[PDB]
Length: 245
Image (cartoon, rainbow, N blue to C red; front, top):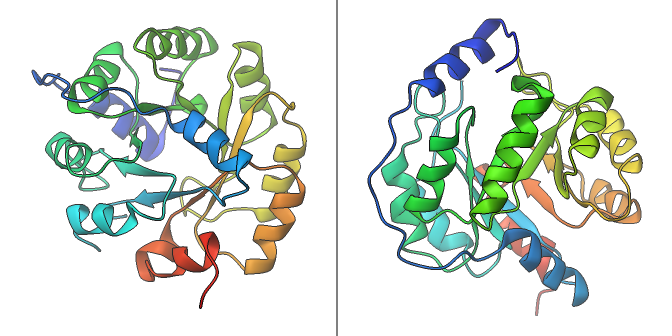
């Protein structure tokens, strides 16, 4: 990992000691970025439901089964200490729903990508701010070796410069204060506009005005990863993806 301080250094050093699981994958890779592109072809709004067991609360299996008919995919956060995630939580979800599952964690070694594949996840999140440029490229290639196109978390211009240099094709835009969780919506749109046409772009939204969705659509975002709004009111995803009777 790169030099880090604060809780980011703590999760990263914790993640380096994450033991690998001895599970065997029981279903194929269901590509997340390809399903998003299939949604785009049919102009279906693609929403990744971003799930946390806790945050510094919904049942993980019930939340996943509720989102299955609506979400383009699920983001499951498997970090244990700060987010109450677990690998067994991911395995149960992956074998219970039929939509793509993204393992969201602080991935700092190859065995974590081995775990995601073995547990049934369809892709992983790679986090630019915790990795060196060479590390991120190596983990990107390793994830691709499994058939996974990882989602690259960028938070500022420097992160994007690194992501594009190593050939990222699937990028999520946080623009988040990692100490508070607050998202700068203005800097988020700005980074989105700097991303070339051949990259699948996914802004992260905790809360949002429905007007902000249409504005992001104008910038050419392929999907939306939505966290706290859907945790508080899961039924709000229906308004995003379908009309009413």
